[PDB]
Length: 48
Length: 48
Ligand SMILES: *[C@@H]1O[C@H](CO)[C@@H](O[C@@H]2O[C@H](CO)[C@@H](O)[C@H](O)[C@H]2NC(C)=O)[C@H](O)[C@H]1NC(C)=O
Ligand SMILES: *[C@@H]1O[C@H](CO)[C@@H](O)[C@H](O)[C@H]1NC(C)=O
Image (spheres, chains in turn red, cyan):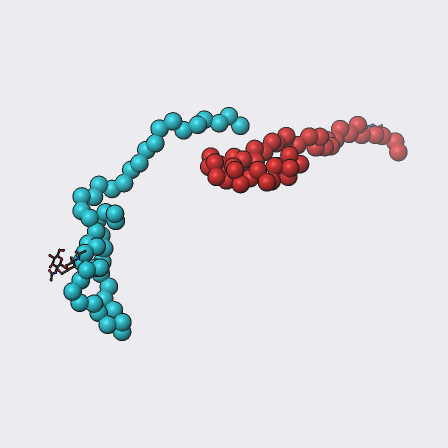
C-alpha cells in the first residue's frame, strides 16, 4: 500500500435489560380475598 | 404492592317494582303437555 484510510466504525452491544418485579397476588388474584386465600398453597413457587 | 381496602358497599340494580308471577307459572290451573310445552317470557320483575 501507498496510502491509508483512517476508519471509524460503530459497534452496538447490549449491556443490560429491563429490571422487572412481579406481585403474584395482584396478577393471579387481583383484589379478591378468596383467590388470595386459595393462593397460600402456592407461595413457595412465587417466592421462587 | 400498595393495597387499599374497600370501605363502603355499592349495590346497583335496575329499579323494579313488581314481583315475578310465581303464582301464574307454579299455581296455574292447567299445564301444557310435554310435546306442546308452553314457554312464558319473564321480564321486569323481582325474583324473590
Ligand atoms: C292456587 O290456586 C288455588 C285455586 O284458586 C288456591 O286454592 C284456594 O286457596 C284459598 C286460600 O287458601 C282457599 O280459600 C280456596 O278454597 C282454595 N280453592 C279454590 C278453588 O279457590 C291455592 O291457594 C292457590 N295457591 C297459591 C300459592 O296461590
Ligand atoms: C492519500 O489519499 C488522500 C485522500 O484520502 C490524498 O489527499 C493524499 O494525497 C493521498 N496520498 C498519497 C497518494 O500519497
